[PDB]
Length: 99
Length: 99
Ligand SMILES: CCC[C@@]1(CCc2ccccc2)CC(O)=C([C@H](CC)c2cccc(NS(=O)(=O)c3ccc(C(F)(F)F)cn3)c2)C(=O)O1
Ligand SMILES: [Cl-]
Ligand SMILES: [Cl-]
Image (cartoon, rainbow over all chains, first blue to last red; front, side, top):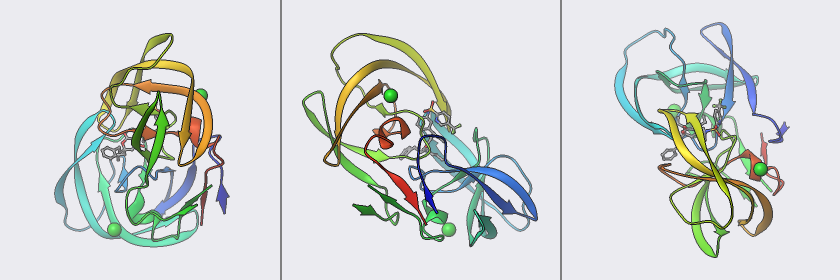
């Protein structure tokens, strides 16, 4: 698709068999989801946003569908205000910026 | 151009007589720049994102050039960790997400 930016680029994602709404965010290195449970081991990470730093849990090699496009990669979980899809997964689905 | 997302989408902007590096951020409602002087009236604003809220100065009707494309819009100025071009200006330069 082509997504214009007059509204927030919110899309449906599927993770763990469940649908969620998430923001396509070209300013995010990483994908960060609101508190939830994921299987497997996790490792710690500190990430920065516009307001400062947050602690998150890093899960690797997680299956996640974004606008119907299948990705498998790193998902961070922590106190983000919205589910954010960052560049690590935007590149997996072939996303570019165009103007 | 067509900008891929393997690295942060940083571009050159021209604003208030200055050349700066800024991040094209489809996740940001607003454009927020690190501390700088801008002409005219301003009012305080709180903006929130990852890590919480920061207080910024809101300047309206500010001319800007982003990667060679002219626009006008609101520019916020405050303690953001990086200069961020948000949707309010990305729309004006015809920026879309494509996959
Ligand atoms: C996972 C962190 C993502 C990010 C990283 C910024 C960064 C980049 C390089 C180095 C250091 C830091 C980019 C980003 O879009 C935001 C948020 C949106 C999720 C953001 C950015 C800019 C302004 C705002 N405030 S706002 O009022 O314009 C606003 C508020 C809320 C939302 C919502 F969509 F997230 F709800 C979008 N915009 C928020 C942020 O807080 O940090
Ligand atoms: Cl990844
Ligand atoms: Cl505006």
